[PDB]
Length: 263
Ligand SMILES: O=C(Nc1cccc(-c2nnn[nH]2)c1)c1cccc2nc[nH]c12
Image (tube, rainbow, N blue to C red; front, top):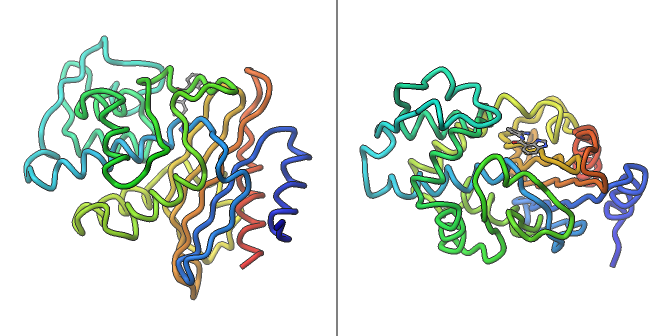
């Protein structure tokens, strides 16, 4: 079937010129709304959630892991390092790296998370351990954002990512302490106000992680507490046909608005 909401999302997609993927889980009733829910999209920096969560999982059996220092060398800096560049020739802890990756979208910090997990495949292994058979991380930053149409590397589907984000933030994929830390980090994101959150009523609250890459790829994944309602999990992924296309955070906002209006 095609619902009213799916029809509205299709119309948004058509006027955007790109390809839109949406997955909602409403934890009021566990129902789902999907649009291209089983198509693959480049994750870009939304993959930082999986990496940080995998390190949180490791910390369950090492109480001091998040206080562990990681050397930041001049050679480690990549293309977007607003936090790590302050610490070059010094150290950051794994908590600091997780917070920088999630809240500032620092790519050097993400690379240290990936290295802590033994490379991109360590992030995929954690996804499999928590029931996500779809997610794959194949490369480090910055090349994981190439976002080439048809390229399976560094992709997932909206359905899989929504289910994962639910399990991480609201369910029991992590220990209680760790889940609370992940939620705190997401709620403190600095980069999200133009994306999903711009489409929601202002009384609501949320935590999110954005991403962007080539092909005008513009992504956001969020856990949302609507006023007076059980929480939602929402993924909005968007990618465009030309390598040099401009980001379109407004499309994510519009998708979120359609979703919110359909509750
Ligand atoms: O690392 C990249 N982008 C990047 C770096 C750091 C953070 C983000 C980001 N976070 N939230 N939304 N975008 C995006 C990047 C790499 C290669 C080609 C790209 N074209 C656009 N961005 C690209």
